[PDB]
Image (cartoon, rainbow over all chains, first blue to last red):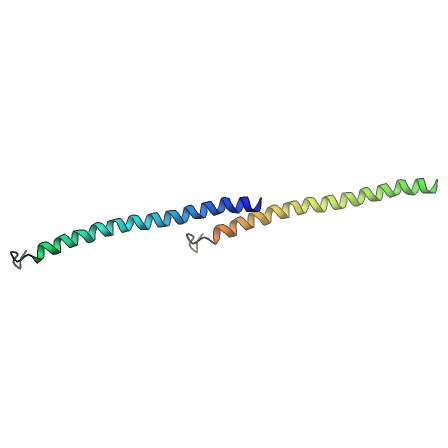
Length: 54
Length: 54
């Protein structure tokens, strides 16, 4: 009965660690989207056609 | 006749010993339930998702 209760808590604890990993990965999702946008703007800005104003 | 009376008293003393042992065990029944709950809380607190507040 002590092990059964401890396994109930253990499943709750694995779910909580699942949630922290989920929330973090979701935040990294927008970090990837933002970084890719910077990369496209960097390629565009490297073109020789561009002047200094743009 | 003396042994018959002393045996009647002996059953009374055996029953009183049963009563005391029974009560002491009923109290230890709740000591077990309280300790098991304390163990569930400790397992939950050992999780890393918790902050100092929890």
